[PDB]
Image (spheres, coloured by chain):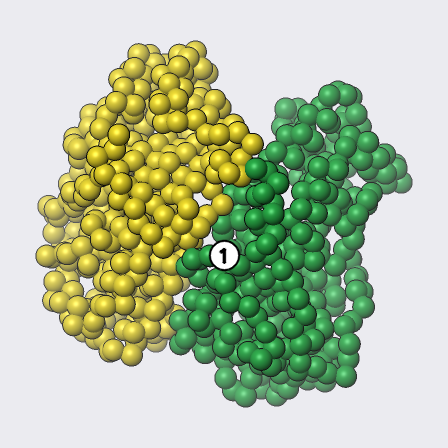
Chain colours: A green, B yellow
């Protein structure tokens, strides 16, 4: 019953090295489209000048050709976006076109030459974006001054260091065909630079509270649980405390974001968690059931499956290990993180 | 027992099964005089029933009074984990009916104010949509009936005056949902089953006021409306949506290219009203004649037409990816268009001669400027 369903999902889920990159594969029989996602390890936090977002714009260009125009003529919409630690290149298409579209995409991503006219043109485009969540977007876009201090040598060096197969994760969701090196020879287009070390530079009106007590998967469970618990208590008591989440694939720990003005009310609610002894145990039981229900519902949408692969590293981990981590969260884990949150809020 | 089992094979295999019932309210939704009452009671019923039915293995319960081509329909839906993958079997359709009839009247009264405020806010936010308000004000005047535009989600004055004595119309609504004849849809095992052959006869309102000018004075946008004559199912469901993407959506659309000479453009085909709208944010006076002359002298070519076919197929494929988009498609479409494969094949078989038939049947009907 429940065990056979997790086994069903896991037999369609796989991850293997292809060339010098890794491809996470979730096959769906008779899906109408296939989602392909190329995720490069560089975002707004890897370099705080907006360089990653600048590179994302440059990556659409190769020898005067724009890959969005090439994909559009092939009937596919290429979408790109930069988050705090990654840059995503995502598109949907029929499975017969996946191999050629993917290899054409990696052809652009592993191109490392950008003339001055292309750099200056994209700078003007990005400055118009800066002049046109809000703190997160402007941090990714950078400022007009910060991107104006980077030239061709920097962008090309950054491309060679970060846009490599070793620093790339590929996710292909839907269909039934396997991804291999013969069809994507660009998966070996390497440079002299290996995978960059996970340097982060998390840079004053908010506080960042760590959720770190257990394995990588456990931290996501606890972080979602405590954030959901605090929001529920803030509703009944009609507070106005927003609780943001910092959950990144390259971070072993998870983090809660709360306004520094709302620190007092949030601190009170954290201490309010351990009041009702049955509240934590019943909310964990409700969350475990809700998590499984949402996963069953979400595993029909290609993009939602992709979000599980990036948040929970599904592929490296099985769905069995995901639910095993979920089922292992007890009230003692919550109380332990409750204590470390209170210690962080004290100082 | 069902009279038929219309099994459509080749469907995407989903993680859940779906059991849906579509009950026909044959009269056009403007002819229903208790429209605001029926909407409010249905949402109240849905909320109460959901609390009792949305337990394992049921993941989501759906009950709405929906409009499909200007005809009211009660649509009951059940999303659930398949029995082979669920620790508990799903209730039958008879037990779901029994849950609806076992709804307590005090439970409905507990939801009255919340449901009333929910629907009131939907009426306001749908009316308070500027770019669509131009389309709303046009549809109001083009059809001489506010039920097609402003009062489409219900009239505000009628909905805001509902009191809790609407509880006494709950037996009539429960009877209509449980005992009214309808079609059953069942998605399972990569197939969708339909209980009977029946095509919902479409209704499109006729334009009464032709050539509407919404001269509106306000301080800090334009909207033009077009229609088509002799509309076939192929046009309303495939060709015209392709035409809308051709002229105001698919990348370098005809309107973006035309209006970039002047130097925030949108277009949408309303299948309910058979109206193609074009919304664009002093300078609007030149854009008015520039848009009109562009649609009058519209031309096509087979290379760009083949790309619009590919794009619209992939957009339809993306809707079929969603189990609700698939279900809604199989409910609404006529005959063989219910089969997604047949619908996709019908897109692939369109030819450019179809666009010139559509251009000859196209005309302007209204314009709204704020
Ligand atoms: Ni951008």
Q: Is residue A181 left or right of residue B140?
A: right
Identify which residue is drawn at 22% across, 28% down: B181
Could you say which is closer to the camera, residue B210 or residue A227? A227
Residue B264 seen: yes
- Residue A209, compared with residue A160, is above or below; it is above
Q: Is residue A331 left or right of residue A30?
A: right
Could you say which is closer to the camera, residue A262 or residue B271? B271
Identify which residue is drawn at 61% across, 80% down: A186
- Residue A160, compared with residue B80, is above or below; it is below
Indicate the quadrant where residue A89 lies: bottom right
Report if the beta carbon of the residue with label 1 is closer than 8 angstroms to ligand 1. Answer: no
Could you say which is closer to the camera, residue B321 or residue A56? B321
Q: Chain of mark 1?
A: A
Q: Is residue A144 left or right of residue A91?
A: right
Task: From the top left corner, tell me how far across and down residue B62 is, in percent.
Answer: 40, 33
As helix, strand or loop, the secondary structure at mark 1 comes to loop
Q: Residues within 10 Å of mark 1 (few under 14, many from 20)?
A: many
Identify which residue is drawn at 49% across, 71% down: A98
Judging by the rendered image, the residue that carries numbered circle 1 is A28
Indicate the quadrant where residue A226 lies: top right
- Residue A194, compared with residue A38, is above or below; it is below
């Amino acid at each position: 019953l429940n065990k056979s369903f997790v086994k069903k999902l896991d037999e369609s889920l796989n991850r293997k090295q292809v060339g010098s990159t890794n491809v996470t594969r979730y096959k769906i029989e008779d899906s109408y489209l296939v989602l392909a996602a190329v995720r490069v390890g560089i975002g707004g936090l890897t370099y705080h000048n907006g360089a990653a977002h600048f590179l994302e714009h440059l990556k659409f260009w190769r020898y005067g050709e724009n890959i969005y125009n090439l994909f559009f003529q092939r009937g596919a919409i290429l979408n790109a976006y930069t988050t705090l630690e990654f840059t995503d290149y995502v598109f949907l298409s029929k499975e017969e076109s996946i191999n050629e579209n993917l290899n054409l995409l990696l052809t652009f991503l592993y191109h490392h030459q950008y003339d001055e006219k292309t750099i200056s043109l994209e700078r003007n485009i990005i400055i118009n974006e800066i002049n046109g969540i809000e703190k997160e977007r402007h941090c990714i876009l950078g400022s007009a001054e910060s991107i104006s201090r980077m030239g061709r040598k920097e962008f090309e060096l950054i491309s060679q260091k970060y846009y490599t197969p070793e620093n790339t994760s590929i996710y292909v969701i839907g269909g039934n065909q396997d991804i291999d090196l013969f069809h994507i020879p660009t998966a070996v287009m390497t440079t002299q630079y290996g995978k960059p070390t996970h340097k982060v530079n998390v840079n004053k009106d908010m506080i960042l509270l760590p959720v770190e007590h257990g394995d990588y998967l456990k931290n996501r469970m606890i972080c979602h649980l405590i954030a959901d618990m605090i929001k529920h208590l803030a509703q009944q008591l009609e507070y106005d405390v927003s609780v943001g989440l910092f959950i990144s694939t390259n971070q072993h720990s998870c983090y809660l974001k709360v306004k520094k003005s709302d620190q007092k009310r949030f601190s009170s609610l954290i201490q309010q968690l351990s009041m009702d002894e049955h509240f934590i145990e019943t909310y964990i039981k409700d969350y475990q059931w809700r998590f499984m229900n949402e996963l069953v519902i979400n595993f029909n949408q290609l993009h939602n499956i992709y979000d599980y692969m990036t948040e929970y590293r599904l592929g490296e981990y099985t769905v069995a290990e995901l639910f095993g981590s979920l089922d292992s969260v007890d009230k003692l884990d919550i109380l332990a993180v409750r204590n470390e949150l209170i210690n962080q809020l004290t100082v | 027992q069902d009279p038929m089992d219309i099994k459509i094979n080749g469907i995407k295999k989903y993680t859940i099964h779906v059991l849906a019932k579509v009950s026909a309210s044959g009269m056009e939704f403007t002819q229903e005089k208790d429209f605001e009452h029926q909407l409010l009671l249905t949402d109240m019923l849905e909320t109460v029933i959901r609390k009792s039915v949305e337990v394992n293995p049921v993941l989501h319960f759906h009950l709405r009074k929906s409009i499909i081509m200007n005809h009211s329909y009660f649509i009951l839906g059940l999303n659930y984990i398949p029995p082979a993958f669920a620790t508990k079997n799903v209730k039958s359709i008879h037990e779901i009916y029994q849950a609806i009839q076992d709804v307590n009247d005090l439970q409905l009264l507990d939801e009255f104010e919340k449901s009333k405020e929910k629907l009131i806010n939907k009426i306001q936010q749908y009316k308070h949509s500027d770019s669509h308000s131009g389309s709303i004000r046009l549809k109001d005047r083009l059809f001489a009936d506010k039920k097609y535009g402003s009062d489409r989600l219900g009239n505000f004055e009628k909905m805001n005056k509902i009191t809790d004595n609407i509880i006494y119309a709950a037996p009539d609504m429960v009877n209509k949902i449980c005992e009214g004849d309808g079609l059953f849809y069942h998605i399972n095992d990569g197939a969708i089953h339909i209980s009977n052959i029946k095509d919902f006869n479409y209704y499109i309102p006729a334009v009464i006021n032709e050539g509407v000018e919404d001269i509106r004075t306000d301080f800090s946008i334009l909207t033009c409306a077009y229609t088509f004559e002799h509309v076939t199912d192929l046009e309303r469901e495939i060709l015209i949506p392709m035409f809308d993407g051709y002229i105001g959506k698919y990348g370098h659309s005809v309107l973006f290219k035309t209006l970039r000479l002047v130097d925030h453009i949108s277009s949408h085909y309303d299948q309910e009203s058979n109206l193609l709208f074009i919304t664009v944010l002093n300078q609007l006076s030149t854009i008015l004649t520039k848009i009109q002359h562009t649609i009058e002298s519209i031309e096509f070519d087979s290379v760009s037409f083949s790309l619009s076919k590919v794009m619209f197929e992939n957009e339809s494929r993306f809707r079929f990816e969603d189990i609700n988009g698939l279900l809604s498609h199989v409910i609404k479409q006529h005959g063989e268009y219910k089969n997604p494969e047949s619908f996709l094949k019908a897109i692939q078989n369109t030819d450019i001669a179809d666009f010139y038939r559509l251009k000859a049947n196209m005309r302007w009907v209204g314009t709204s400027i704020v």
